[PDB]
Length: 508
Ligand SMILES: [Mg+2]
Image 1: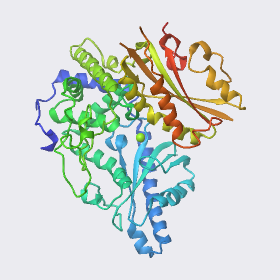
Image 2: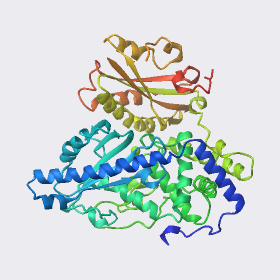
Image 3: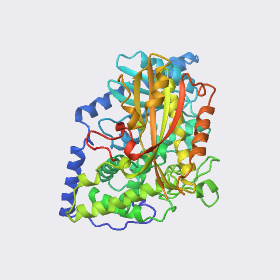
Image 4: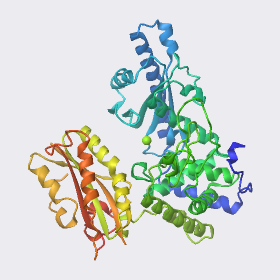
């Protein structure tokens, strides 16, 4: 049974009463920490999805009519919404976006999605916000609609109709699709497979809710900065579910930390045998592809074509993940022996207390929210490259990127003030000299914690290269009247208080 994975179960023993009690405690702690939304919020999501399906049909219909098709053929053309990622898995929370895919027949172009479908959304009274990003890895429209955040992508099939009955599991659907359409289909195909690959979906969901919370709190969740993201975490949980098909989620978590802490990296985590299929694309294969051999902690997607979802993991972030696995073993063991609580497991990281030195990376923009989102996105996208350059330097013991940029915005009349913002920010010694308060200047700041092992050592070259790289991406970047980029080396005693919550106090 594929549900027991590629190695067979470790144990088919069922949960005991004591284990189920630990599981009840685990669920109550998840509830206390806000993991679950209300029944009303779930209803609200279901309603917006009905509307999205209606609009997806209307979109395909309108495009079809514009290309001179009869009413019947335009109806027949169809159009269908799917969800993927956390909502589709049922592990979403009150804040969560719905990752949503719009699948359209062959005559409906990506251009049509960004014009006709985009306009259909803008005509709705329920639309709160809309931000099209036709450039992203997967071209996307991000919206808020009746208060719910929806992330919308589009895939064009090589068939003239998209009926309501359509499922995406048939790998023949991938024939004749361009790279972007393949990418677009991959998310939903993988999510759907993960669900079919675990022995008991609700055990999986509770375990994954816990790992998502744990990973966010422990600052090991962010694919962009070299940590596993949602799909990778989902697959790691799924693997352990297969090994203990009759276990309770609390037991899955204990076994998870142990197994992954002890695992023989770079040996891969795989949920089902790697499939071949009808395309000429490479499937993950460290035997024959040197890039694949380089993956440090490979977590491989099950849907054809299999790929490594954790390719971004670096030398430094691997160490952090493994450290966090070890803490998890210690703590869950203690919870099982009734010495510690689930709340102990989910305690927030102490990133800003644990290093003597930090590198601050600040992306400034003076203009619209749009070009800042684009600029910072760009700068944010390169941070992992700086980490890889820093971490291989002789003097550097670790270069540990934080997982979330600190965001800020300001009243910036001149022209002068933008200059003054770039100056007093990043150090607690000079930061107080800000206000008001908060025409606008944006900031995104990433932090890299540094551990060094005649002192120094000199990190300025990779830093300068990083700045030059980010400026290179177009002539605008590039400017200096609008876009700017700063790297600052700070001691821990001198970190800005944006970095501590009103719950901790700064070290010295
Ligand atoms: Mg998302």
